Image (tube, helix red, strand yellow):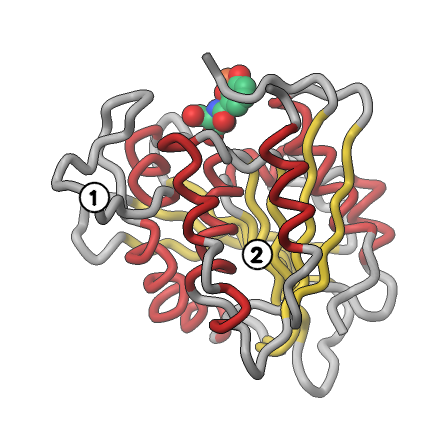
Amino acid sequence: SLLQRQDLPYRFSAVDLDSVDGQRHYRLWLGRPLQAPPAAGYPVVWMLDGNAAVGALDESTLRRLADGDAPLLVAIGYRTPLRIDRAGRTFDYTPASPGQADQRDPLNGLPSGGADAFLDLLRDGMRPAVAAQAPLDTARQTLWGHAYGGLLVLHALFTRPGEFARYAAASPSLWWRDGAILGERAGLEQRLRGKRAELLLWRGSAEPASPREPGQAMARLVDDLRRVAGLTLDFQPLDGLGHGETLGASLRLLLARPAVE
Ligand SMILES: O=C(N[C@@H](CO)C(=O)O)c1cccc(O)c1O
Ligand SMILES: [Fe+3]
């Protein structure tokens, strides 16, 4: 319903692209404020699982976002009949395992390891297409994701910091490949030299540790990252919520934060 609606201070339009290999099909939903852009361009919020993200963007949030410094919203979705692509997101949101050649997801068995190709496409194809539709302030960009989307967000921050000002990971799948993402954090302070980033983290109080000790891995990660120079960290636990529900909750709360400086 939201994408057709005409009563909000945002208008949504679609920008379509394929992956470089031709196997995955994207539709970016662009939400542009009626408000004129600042001289330096709109700040930008990029959202993974874009078809689900659009379903969570409520009217009250969107009215308040039009506050004189409203962001451009870019929801990166799959352009499929079903409006999901389990294979596509499994490949696009997971890092490669240097260990071996068996790049298959340990849970669902589908090909994995496409995170760097996905982030390269965002940089080299998606942003070019979005910037042609609306002026962007490239110093004021946010990347948000939930679950495997949050895994991709942490991969981006940990291995290629500086592409975004603010990283936002909701219920990231820290269990993935027995904690492999936690290894990628080693070396971050060196990679952040001369740069600044903000990381927002959420987890629901009712979530298990994995889909098959709850909270422990996140608590350890938070404790570690609080020590990292150049990184501003904000962890928000979500009392009363389980795994599915932290998607909408995190996005509402993100969009209520002060805009990136
Ligand atoms: O990370 C989870 N699921 C992912 C699929 O592997 C996802 O991306 O949601 C996950 C975590 C805790 C509990 C769950 O039921 C769950 O699906
Ligand atoms: Fe689950």
Quadrant showing the N terminus: top right
Q: Cα distance, mark 1 to mark 2?
A: 28 Å
- Residue at 61% in and 23% down: 244
Residue on which disc 1 sits: 99
| 177 sits to left or right of 222 | left
Q: Nearer the viewer, residue 149 or 34?
A: 149
Cβ at disc 2 under 8 Å from ligand 1: no
Q: Is residue 14 above or below residue 164?
A: above
Mark carried by residue 191? none
Residue on which disc 2 sits: 143
Q: Is residue 186 above or below residue 238?
A: below
* Mark closest to the chain's N terminus, 1 or 2: 1
Q: Is residue 95 above or below residue 119?
A: above
Residue lying at the far bottom of the rendered structure: 39
Q: Which mark lies nearer to you, 1 or 2?
A: 1
Percent from the top left, x then y, of residue 257? 81, 55
Q: Amino acid at mark 1?
A: Gly
Percent from the top left, x then y, of residue 49? 49, 39
Quadrant showing the C terminus: bottom right
Q: Nearer the viewer, residue 32 or 242?
A: 242
- Residue at 75% in and 38% down: 58
Residue lying at the far top of the rendered structure: 212
Q: Nearer the viewer, residue 103 or 63?
A: 103
Looking at the rendering, which quadrant does residue 178 occupy? top left
Q: Amino acid at mark 2?
A: Leu
> At numbered mark 2, what does the secondary structure look like: helix, strand or loop?
strand
